[PDB]
Length: 141
RNA sequence: CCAUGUAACAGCAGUUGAACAUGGGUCAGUCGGUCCUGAGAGAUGGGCGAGCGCCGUUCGAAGGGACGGGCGAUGGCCUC
Image 1 (cartoon, rainbow, N blue to C red):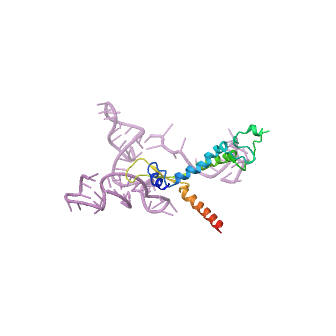
Image 2 (cartoon, rainbow, N blue to C red):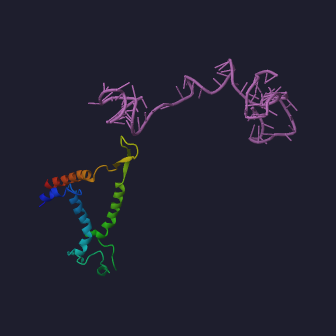
Image 3 (cartoon, rainbow, N blue to C red):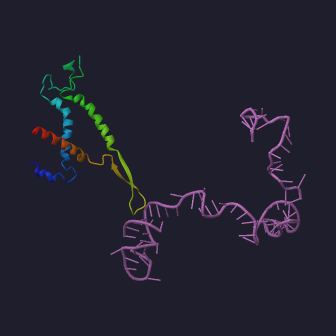
């Protein structure tokens, strides 16, 4: 099933290295999280088939500060947007190094040395893999 | 000059160059200039000259500077 897709996706825009798969599924758990509430059929203890973001008839008085132990869709979105804003701010940090052609007098370019200077996959995976390797070892043992 | 890089020129050639291109390099109280006048040049006074000017350089009321004393220095209020 996936062997055929392995070689074809690389050609073109450049959505290869399997990272295009990771972003699609990772963002999916974030974006379809909102759409889960209207489509959720399980209730547990409170009605959910009609959604929980707007439930004024069910609650109301109305306790807007509900228990966010399941479907925290109301509160986690508040905190996550803060993380999105802070990361992009630190993403733009870089030290610009003056650079010029060794033959032509004129335009000056800058070699950018990013603050991270390493793609997130090489750094975070090396810490993600060891965390996964630790867990599987303890589960087996 | 230094480094790096590389058709015309280096009366052959060049992978080389005092060539071409890009970019760097010369740090002073103590080494010089700056100060002195030397042969000399040249203002002012004066004279000459139609005149721009030039002759003259010692041939004119050419000192503007001195610690010391009083009015007033009073200023710090009088040490200097």
